[PDB]
Amino acid sequence: IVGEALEYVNIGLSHFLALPLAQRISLIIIIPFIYNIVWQLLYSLRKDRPPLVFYWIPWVGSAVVYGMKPYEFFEECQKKYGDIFSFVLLGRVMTVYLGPKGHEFVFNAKLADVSAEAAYAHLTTPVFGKGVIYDCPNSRLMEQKKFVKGALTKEAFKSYVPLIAEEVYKYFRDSKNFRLNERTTGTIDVMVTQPEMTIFTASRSLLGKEMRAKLDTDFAYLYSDLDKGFTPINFVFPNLPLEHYRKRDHAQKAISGTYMSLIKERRKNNDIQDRDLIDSLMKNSTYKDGVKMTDQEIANLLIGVLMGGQHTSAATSAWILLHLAERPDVQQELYEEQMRVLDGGKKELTYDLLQEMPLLNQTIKETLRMHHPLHSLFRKVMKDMHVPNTSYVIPAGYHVLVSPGYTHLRDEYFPNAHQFNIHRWNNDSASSYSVGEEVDYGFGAISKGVSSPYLPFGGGRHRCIGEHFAYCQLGVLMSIFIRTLKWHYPEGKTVPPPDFTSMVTLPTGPAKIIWEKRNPEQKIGGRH
Ligand code: HEM
Ligand SMILES: CCCN(CCOc1c(Cl)cc(Cl)cc1Cl)C(=O)n1ccnc1
């Protein structure tokens, strides 16, 4: 007789529901806390699952330590478990595969196994708009990248270089942070100057003179509002109604509206040349199945393409300025390269001459090695994936996290990895290179192997298409900085540590350097 025991299950439940509000709250906390803990212990039994990092608080998982110092988190985990391990992150299970094998396993994964758009769309679609990037099937993305690459050709870069140079000089002339016709020395915050210099140079050359002229007005404020939707807090709550969410949505309509306006006027005048990305997409945005991109979609694609490049590039020139500020030896060497290639300054900077500045391109390369703008790249796992040479299975619904930026900082692949050393790239100054066989996903032949320990631009179907644009812009900018200014730190200041909490891993500010003119009496012409 134990039906008598079932009587007391019933009675027991009855007394549960009758406990005071204090104990019941105490229990709605202690009961998932405990379940979680035995669940992990039970989980670590399975040999077909990668090791899972232990955590106390349910749902939150390892969010706090990962969110604040993800490379230290990765390293500590790698010591305990090796290169494959999992951890819970605000609701989700992230499986990290560290090292070159990890790049291979994730970047070169089969289309059917993983989805970038499933990982990213909830974050990007509201910022950029509907119908493009991650708000469309992968095949559509592939053709958009193709369309955009058509405004990123060598001949495009030859015409961008003087426009970008004009903008840097205008900024030296007019911005309160410099004013080189009035001041010979000054303090700047690189996280104030570099985003402005970036948006100004990127706008003028990819969007055109009209759009660049709008940045001189209050309209510029909308791009900032748009940033606030592109944060690792929309990370988790994609849409819950308070005000910076509205300003985001408002900015998107307003900016896309403006782009659509210029598009429609250019077509109404047949004022369609080869100046911009705008001209380019208007002439070339028909998918292979014959469907044309709408004017809304084109405008949304413009926002998305310029947003990403804006923050990665601005963060990178800020890090460059910061590393160089304590290396007058490297400024000196870069300066000598400038005098030699540009014949004392008597040659005008062109895209061709940029390619003959290996030490400048190595400086960019090395900065990107020590400061990858994105410490983590994600895919949602769509089908149970087996991990080669293990018994590990990664179930659908998990996420895979790859981190080439972590490998960038390993001594095994980069001797003295925490040292800024541009000469480690002697006779290897290329932004990237395919050491063999290629493949084409729809936007041109890129490398098939994604095993390089140096992968600032990722690889596989989702690979960056902006690398050459970014070197062009960073190149021109840094060439003018070097030729015009020397700079150094305020007393006792040094290279700041990264802030990893933002979307990109910019430096912890205020990040200030002191500039001074190389030629105090040099004037920059033009009306203002
Ligand atoms: C230093 C500058 C940059 C760095 C380090 C960088 C890095 C990256 C990385 C790592 C990815 C791959 C993301 C993933 O696989 O999850 C990517 C993708 C991409 N980037 Fe860049 N990027 C930079 C600048 C730019 C610029 C200037 C542009 C445009 C002109 C651009 C446009 C794109 C596009 C369209 C993708 C495709 C993403 C996809 O297919 O899912 N990026 N970038
Ligand atoms: C253009 C579509 C979104 N992208 C590409 C994917 O960007 C990412 C990356 Cl690389 C990581 C995470 Cl965590 C989220 C997003 Cl949206 C960009 O804005 N970027 C950023 C740098 N280069 C391009």
Image (spheres, helix red, strand yellow):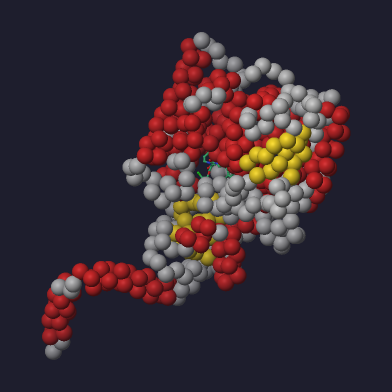
Query: Where does the N terminus fall, quadrant-wise?
Result: bottom left
Whether residue 458 is visible to the viewer of this picture, yes or no, is no
Image quarter for residue 74? bottom right
**Residue shown at 65% from the left, 37% from the top:** 470
Residue 19: percent from left, percent from top: 18, 74
Image quarter for residue 22? bottom left
Q: Does 53 sit left or right of 280 as displayed?
A: left
Name, please, the residue furthest toward the top: 269
Whether residue 89 is visible to the viewer of this picture, yes or no, is yes
**Residue shown at 70% from the left, 47% from the top:** 490
Query: Where does the C terminus fall, quadrant-wise?
Result: top right
Query: Which residue is nearer to you in this view: 243 or 116?
Result: 243
Q: Does 310 sit left or right of 127 as displayed?
A: right
The answer to whether 387 is drawn above or below residue 217 in the figure is below
Residue 509: percent from left, percent from top: 59, 48
**Residue shown at 47% from the left, 56% from the top:** 399
Q: Does 200 sit left or right of 66 as displayed?
A: right
Query: Which residue is nearer to you in this view: 480 or 311?
Result: 480
Residue 65: percent from left, percent from top: 51, 62
Query: Which residue is nearer to you in this view: 342 or 508?
Result: 508
The answer to whether 64 is drawn above or below residue 171 in the figure is below
User: How many labels were placed on the picture?
Assistant: 0
Residue 363: percent from left, percent from top: 74, 44
